[PDB]
Amino acid sequence: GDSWDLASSVGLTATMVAAARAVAGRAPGALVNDQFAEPLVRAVGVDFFVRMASGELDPDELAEDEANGLRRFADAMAIRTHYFDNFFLDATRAGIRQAVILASGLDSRAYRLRWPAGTIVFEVDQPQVIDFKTTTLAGLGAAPTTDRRTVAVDLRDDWPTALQKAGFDNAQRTAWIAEGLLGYLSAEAQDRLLDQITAQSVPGSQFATEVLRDINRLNEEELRGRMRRLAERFRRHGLDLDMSGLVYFGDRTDARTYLADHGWRTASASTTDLLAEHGLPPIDGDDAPFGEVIYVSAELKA
Ligand SMILES: [Mg+2]
Ligand SMILES: [Mg+2]
Image (cartoon, rainbow, N blue to C red):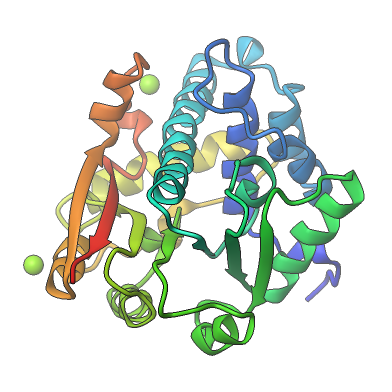
């Protein structure tokens, strides 16, 4: 209530993952450099994340637990960014010309990926966050690399109706992503979003997302311990962010079951296997505050 401006609507978690993409992009041999992460974080103007994104916060100068936590998170964002980038590039290489980025936040893919002529990319998010990123990148002189259409409706509200109004065509194949979202949703909110995707999809449509397989009652106290130790490290640098209040530890239908029941084929790629494939250090125990993240790609069957 005490701020009114666009940048103050952007969630800390969106800003944090963008700052980590900025760090990842400077690594020698980086899988991906999101060249818009640093300037978007700077525009958000949360000082801690500006210092992180810019490299003013130097991991060589940090206590070992902080330096290791930042390097492993940057590697998690390297693999995640690579995964979702390659999902879209594979989908358009297979003839898909309609893409939807759900809760698009600070995702710069409509400005940095190659999209074939005739592609439309729809971005769905709450209006202030939509308006923030569009105005910020326009002011930096970064034109989109595709026909880009925003849908300024929170995923909690009637976004399908607004997506149709923006010119979405439910008769052609769609490539959907929901990146960094499903672990923050209730079981009911997850099933509703997967119903909405399915209802707007024709066969040959594709969807990529994550399954946070370890966020459950079995592992709750261990993961809450990781999240409290991380919260303490953030407080030392002037950020108040307790991830434990943002995740749901309760029962749910695994998204992969839910998709299979709705007629999707799925393919699961573990963080463990993607880090090994790309020659990066393992992310486990204390360095995995959400446990093992499973990246999922799905195709709707006829
Ligand atoms: Mg340690
Ligand atoms: Mg069960």
